[PDB]
Length: 121
Ligand SMILES: CCOC(=O)[C@H]1CCc2n[nH]cc2C1
Image (tube, rainbow, N blue to C red; front, side):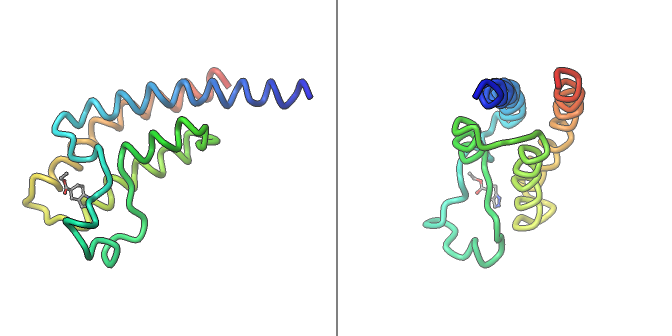
């Protein structure tokens, strides 16, 4: 139907906007601490600690499969990256501090992203 095409056009547009948000957020991680899944080979007990792992590469895979239906779903996954890190790692580690910084700097980006999503529809 024509509706479903228009639908898919918007979803495709959303994906385009989210790809830009994702690139902007990942730029706030120049150390690439959050770029890839936590290695289960190098951290074999990770899943005992963290029930829903997340990372930027995994977000990107879902993004290109157009698997984010709205900004909220995208934001949930970003929050997982931060929150998982701040649980597993102690307050005085480079990892925890990198998560705090990413959350603070990412807030700016996500704030305008929400406006753009509502605005454009
Ligand atoms: C690539 C080196 O960074 C890490 O290992 C940290 C990545 C973020 C994270 N979330 N939970 C545990 C960790 C560990």
